[PDB]
Structure formats: structure tokens, C-alpha cells
Length: 101
Length: 8
Image (cartoon, each protein chain N blue to C red):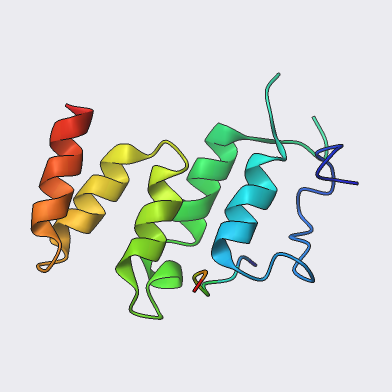
């Protein structure tokens, strides 16, 4: 219902969206464009990394999980710098920067 | 309260 109506943005529907990708997909189907019970890409993209930074998404020591969160929200610079710090994934982060360049 | 469990 609230995937069709883009409502109840605060309720993460955790009963059915238990994975991270299920959350991203749940919200990107809820973002809106031009006051209550409404979320926009700017709020969502900022809300995610500002409040729930790397710390929240890298506790499982899985780096790509956070990268996908930033890249699939149009925050390409964040995801590039972030992934560029993983000494094992420097190569990959430089190139995804070149492509964007 | 988003989960941190990656789709595996």
C-alpha cells in the first residue's frame, strides 16, 4: 500500500524489508519531488550517511554494502572516497572515479 | 532503523 502510495516513510516495513537492498528499494519507491509524511532524495541521501554513517553500514566488515548505499543514492563522490580508503579496493575506487570523470 | 545485513 505505501509502496504504491509512497506513505509511512518512517515505517521501514522491517517485517518484509529485512535486507539492506530491500530498504533502499523500499525508500526509493517512497521518495517524492515537490510537507508531512514525505521524503525527498536530498533528505534521504543526506539522512542516510549523516545520521547512519560508515559506522552503521560497516559493522559487519562488508565494504561494498556501504558503497552500494552511496552509489545507488547518487552520492558518487562519497562512495568513491569511501571505497578509495579500503587498501584492498583502491584500484576499483579510482576507476569508478575515472568513469564518472 | 535500516538493517545492515547484505543480501547474500
